[PDB]
Amino acid sequence: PNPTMPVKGAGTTLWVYKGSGDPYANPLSDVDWSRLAKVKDLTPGELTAESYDDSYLDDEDADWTATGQGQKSAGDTSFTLAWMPGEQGQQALLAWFNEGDTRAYKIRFPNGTVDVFRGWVSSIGKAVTAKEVITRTVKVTNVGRPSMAEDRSTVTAATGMTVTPASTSVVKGQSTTLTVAFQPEGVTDKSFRAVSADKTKATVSVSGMTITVNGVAAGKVNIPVVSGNGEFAAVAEITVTAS
Amino acid sequence: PNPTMPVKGAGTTLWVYKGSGDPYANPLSDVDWSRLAKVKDLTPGELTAESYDDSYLDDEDADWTATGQGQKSAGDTSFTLAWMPGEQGQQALLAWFNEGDTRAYKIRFPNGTVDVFRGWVSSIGKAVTAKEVITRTVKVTNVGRPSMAEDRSTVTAATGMTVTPASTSVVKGQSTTLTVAFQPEGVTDKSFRAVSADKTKATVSVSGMTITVNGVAAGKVNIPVVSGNGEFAAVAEITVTAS
Amino acid sequence: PNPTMPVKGAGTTLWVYKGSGDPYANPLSDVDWSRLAKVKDLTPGELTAESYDDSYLDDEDADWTATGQGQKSAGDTSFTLAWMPGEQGQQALLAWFNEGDTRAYKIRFPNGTVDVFRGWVSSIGKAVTAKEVITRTVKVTNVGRPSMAEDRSTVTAATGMTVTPASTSVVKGQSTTLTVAFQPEGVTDKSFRAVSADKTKATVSVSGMTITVNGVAAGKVNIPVVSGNGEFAAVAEITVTAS
Amino acid sequence: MKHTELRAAVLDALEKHDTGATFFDGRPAVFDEADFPAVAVYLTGAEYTGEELDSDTWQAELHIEVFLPAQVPDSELDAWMESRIYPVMSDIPALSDLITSMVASGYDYRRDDDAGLWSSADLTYVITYEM
Amino acid sequence: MKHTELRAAVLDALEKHDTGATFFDGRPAVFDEADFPAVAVYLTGAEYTGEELDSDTWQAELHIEVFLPAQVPDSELDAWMESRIYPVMSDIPALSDLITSMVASGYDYRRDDDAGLWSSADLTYVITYEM
Amino acid sequence: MKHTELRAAVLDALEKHDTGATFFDGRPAVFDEADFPAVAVYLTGAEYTGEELDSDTWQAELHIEVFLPAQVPDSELDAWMESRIYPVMSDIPALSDLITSMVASGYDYRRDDDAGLWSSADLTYVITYEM
Amino acid sequence: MKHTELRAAVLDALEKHDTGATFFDGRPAVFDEADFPAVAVYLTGAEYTGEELDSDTWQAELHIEVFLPAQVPDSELDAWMESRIYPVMSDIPALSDLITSMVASGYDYRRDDDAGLWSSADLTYVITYEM
Amino acid sequence: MKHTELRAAVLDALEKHDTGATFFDGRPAVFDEADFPAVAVYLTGAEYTGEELDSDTWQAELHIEVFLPAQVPDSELDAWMESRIYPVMSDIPALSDLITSMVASGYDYRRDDDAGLWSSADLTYVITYEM
């Protein structure tokens, strides 16, 4: 359950804060969040902004229009769920709408992260027809800066990365695996490529954290490996042999 | 990779500038650009040019609509990609939207031909259903002159990065200056990066088509060099002496 | 390669004038025109005339609207073509857009006819997906009075209408061929009409200027063949026989 | 999962009234002209319509059939369907919690042509169930 | 369902008109070269296109087949379909009260190819009813 | 190449659980009535829906197939898929790292009729992978 | 003409690597049980998608077939069709000049059942070419 | 009708070019193994797409079909088709007068599978014409 790879989406959960303190504190815990069930669909309120203008007469250039980001709005989130009057919480949601207050609701994705927005109810719809269950339609108008999932993310980096030295025994394409891992806690933000300093005797074949170097013609090679940050790097001595 | 032949489009990649210089100087090199992958689809910004009336009652036959283009604009670029909350760069654009500066980004076609636009994020959206990976959609409005690919139209490059090896011992504050230059007779968008592989005994401070190595302590270590976007490399050994 | 028959349409060519003389002078000449290779699709700018009000207070009943043609607009011409950055000339047209001047372009149809417009580029875009080539989108604001190929077309007529005389043997269906040839160089705008003066004893069955005169009953009659122009006509002597 | 009990519950829901028919569960059947007119219950389909972002909410098709010998007129088949099977199953609280939503689809006839060894009427339901 | 009643009603409506043909209800049929030109009445389809949130409102299809000897020219079939069937059922109060809406659907011919023992004409209607 | 890795990963997870079945992987099978109930896993489709501008990102269908002898009641087969396979692919870390995404599509049944030697049920998983 | 040129170019692009197979061009094939695993190349379709106002710009389907004896496991077919033939043809400079674009479409298998003599795997490419 | 001269018109064009084949016109064909490679011309379709308020403007498919001995490789057919037909059918003055529009559709291959006496290359054209 990692946020560093794409995830399906099935298994997402919707929760509504019912406590009193700030929901932004520890949204991961569902202590004071009302869980809803059987949510037919979900449409998060897309983040939107405005094209503020900054034109002036005293301008060297006029043809290319210049504008800046204005003010941003969280839009509206709408979703549908099975009409469940007997459920406890739809009434609270109905009461929320009827009282028209501003409340906070979060979403727990089947990914390991959470997202919570603050707003007030904007629309309630009920669709009725045979051959399929009655559906309850809800739309909420978000307000203010919303707590975003990536803000709760943490990043580990720096301290360099390791490299397996020597690996000079080269014969018939070498095919020697080189491990370039990172010392700090193993987990980090991976950004590193290997580029051969000769490209003739030895050539780098970077393959998913594993370097499978190759050798064609005999020679002494210093294969350098570098990181994405541009700070940490290493060089591996290689004695390529044609035979 | 012939730019004068029709090309499908697979392998296209999108990049966001992260350095502190003009993006338009060296679009080919990706050193100051951060790449975001898993791009679901891409709709490039559309260049616009609204009409401008040019009419006078003291003219000839007024049976036509003599007009000229006025405020040309690159419009906005939109794309979708798989949600990667735990990936470095998704936060960058998210924060980039959050404070709404005017950064530049680069799209690299499978032809060695790239384009650069500067703008601000105008809209952020998240799409999620069952059975389909969560996708995030972002709209950024271009600003100013778009630096489109066809302007350059005259790239030249070849194989080889010249540098001065050895230069091991250095005293009097160390700081030995090592020359680095390109094989393709300088007719190329030059770019290279080099750092100390250990930094424990020697420090490299590459600046202005050359590097300076001021060793903090005696010892031997190799100095990796990466030719900008990562196509060629060289290694210079430095054995700084204590005296 | 005639203009008087419906044309397949596939195979048309697109050119842009690049010299300095009047494009309207010799649109057939391609010397000062650059061919635009790989035209995926084309959409000519339509010709539209604005509706000018003409109703007055003092007149008869104004129950029906009285509007005359107002100012005429050449519309906007759009087309799509394969993205060919390495081609020499695609840079020009976008630069033509970039400079924002008014130029002239012509379309050579697979018929033997060419139409030329004048205008300035207004919209440039590119569409890119997978498993299909990258396409370039262009839209040009046509300006001024454009040159329709109909004006370039000439007129051939007059000199009367020749006719094959005699053929006074009509019996047993018969349908004697009758050729109303047109004097001027053969090539003529054939608008004639043939019809017998009796409609019972003799009749005409003209097909492709080849008139077939049939008969059932005997007697004497003269078959007139006239021109739709209203001043040229011919009359042939026919003596149909029953057997 | 719930397939075993779902067939079990409905077949038990049928057996509460008078007997006079075998209640072959599933499929193997094997009749011979000694265990005649009877009924069979089985399900097909079993797709993964999403329809929901919290649980699988699978959907399958419910087949309930009846078999009669040779060329007995369909009036028996109609009467058998409209009385013996259709009304009783229209409200069986046992499966109410076992399922999510039930809906009828149609009712068809199909009979042996060569040697006319039998004659079958099929009632078909669509079932949404949280497996 | 109400199928037995509806078939009985239409059958009696046909029988009221001047006879000359067998009036087989259902589907067993079995003709032999003695019950020739004759008719059979039956139903197919029987779906649950609900379409209405008050009652089932099922929809079915009515087949009226007329069988004639072997390779009689289709003029007789045209006369039969134009005289004895199509007009007579255009207004029958019994079925009018029995069902909700009845609509003409199609009418066609088909004759036996191998051994050509018969030639049938089919008249099909669509009916909406409530069970 | 991923199929051998993909095929091995799932079968080993299946083999990791309780035994009682042969694990014929791939295609040729060839059973005879000594190596009964056995599971077969294979891939089909594998087209080139582009869908992604930086990598090809194909997708293919994964089959999980298990054979049972003739007229064994489907209740056992329904039990078998639950008792053996279906819950295991809910979370397998092996192929999760191996491929991009994979969802369920359907779960069906079939059997031999002529000589009725075998009876099988198949599991279809749509998988999305890059190669 | 391009088909002879196209077929010639691709087979040469395959043969540059290590051998191990026969390279039947065209279509008539005729294998016999000694010239086994072998590769066939041919084209189908060849329509007139206009798509352009300057040339016919036809499209066709390129088929790469690898044949293996009877009931060998598909594992080698996966290896053969993914490693032996796919990466090599991924970029053939002769084709790039020869054609306008190349797109991958299909990845199939077909096991002989009657007498089960052979086993074929199909790789399908859609080609946009102008002749 | 237009078809006879239409068939005559193309026949003149191909016979005008270099021969090398019989020109059995229409459809009866009947070859025997003496008159090999030869061509044939016929029409299919001929419907009434209105398309025009004043003229009927029918359209139909035109088949240029060439047969080659049994298992001759497609290269000969490819060479035959793209040299001896496609360039010839590029433009014919007679056809332009006769019909309204001339559009290419595509061309395929097929052959006698059982026994295998012949191979066939079929080119299909689209003609829009006014009666």
Image (cartoon, coloured by chain):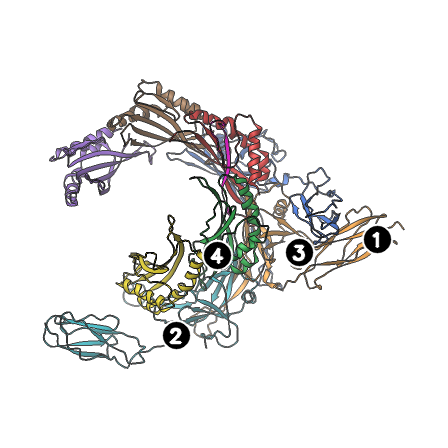
Chain colours: A blue, B orange, C cyan, D brown, E purple, F red, G green, H yellow
Q: Amino acid at mark 4?
A: Thr
Indicate the secondary structure of the residue bearing disc 4.
strand
What residue does disc 4 label? Answer: G128
Question: What distance separates the C-alpha of mark 1 from that of mark 3?
Answer: 30 Å
Magenta part of the protein: which range?
F28-49
What residue does disc 1 label? Answer: B168
Please rate how many residues cluster around mark 1, counting C-alpha atoms within 10 Å: few if below 14, some from 14 to 19, many from 20. Answer: some
Question: What distance separates the C-alpha of mark 2 from that of mark 3?
Answer: 55 Å
Q: Amino acid at mark 1?
A: Thr
Please rate how many residues cluster around mark 3, counting C-alpha atoms within 10 Å: few if below 14, some from 14 to 19, many from 20. Answer: some
Residue A66 is at least partly visible in this image = no
Instruction: Indicate left or right for F27 with H104 as reference.
Output: right
Disc number lying in front (2 or 3): 3
Please rate how many residues cluster around mark 4, counting C-alpha atoms within 10 Å: few if below 14, some from 14 to 19, many from 20. Answer: some
Percent position of residue A213, x then y: 69, 47
The chain identifier of the residue carrying mark 3 reads B
What residue does disc 3 label? Answer: B29
Q: Earlier in the sequence, mark 1 or mark 3?
A: 3
Q: From this view, report whether residue F10 is shown above or below residue E110.
A: above
Disc number lying in front (4 or 1): 4
Indicate the secondary structure of the residue bearing disc 2.
helix
Asked whether the beta carbons under mark 2 and mark 3 sit within 8 Å of each other, the answer is no
The chain identifier of the residue carrying mark 4 reads G
Q: Amino acid at mark 3?
A: Ser
Indicate the secondary structure of the residue bearing disc 3.
loop
Asked whether the beta carbons under mark 1 and mark 3 sit within 8 Å of each other, the answer is no
Q: Which mark is residue G59?
A: none
Disc number lying in front (1 or 3): 1
Disc number lying in front (2 or 4): 4
Same chain shared by disc 2 and disc 4: no
